[PDB]
Image 1 (cartoon, rainbow, N blue to C red):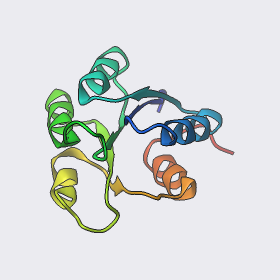
Image 2: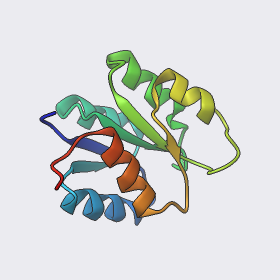
Image 3: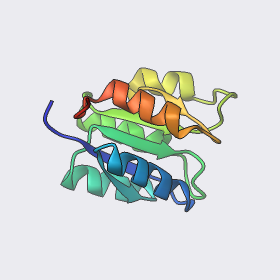
Length: 124
């Protein structure tokens, strides 16, 4: 316990400001990205333990991005965000290296709850 680097990977604007302000006051230094390529760049200059991959990006599937994250360090918690039902490679995704897979529309309460339950942060 002694760090809090998060990386929000996504292109659609809007949610990037929700996870930012929320993880901003809560006490988390999250960043912003888009193409998996960038997510890796910041992951190498920051090496965050929480990586959010949005499969709703208009370009490619982050599925491969994760494979690269775990390959670097199996001790890297990387969450995902896609359909909240049709499990398309979501059940196996975690098996490789993905805590859980949120979806949209999601609730800032369930997001700050799981994250706060995963990584430890100044509380009380």
